[PDB]
Amino acid sequence: RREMQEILPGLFLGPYSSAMKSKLPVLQKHGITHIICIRQNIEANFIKPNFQQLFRYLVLDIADNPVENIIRFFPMTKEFIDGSLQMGGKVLVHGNAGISRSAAFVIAYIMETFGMKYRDAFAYVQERRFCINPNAGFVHQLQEYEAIYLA
Image (cartoon, rainbow, N blue to C red; front, top):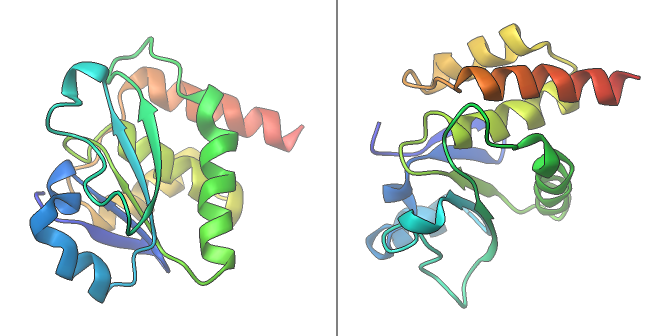
């Protein structure tokens, strides 16, 4: 729960603790080059980019609640992750707990890229990171985005 897991080749999912200063050796050993750092502005005291010069960041100001809009950022994060993986880079996606917001963004990537429905993508990720649980609003938005890209 307090560490990052490889979810699919080159894409890792973790809590904020996985991208703290002290974890640099772990990040470099796994060839991480890009980090999606997700947090509310009120969390920005402890959840923030810690390696200004070493990694490319995407910081997303997102609350973990069922009415928060995350679908607006699915195209952005898909592009960011594709861009890294295409150049042989690797991506860490982290939130606070690595349970709801961060998990939803990894699921969106998996659904679109690997042609999986929500239930199957959720199950796939849960097998790797046992604690994941996107809120219901996020689940609906995942389904809503699939309807978009399938149209």
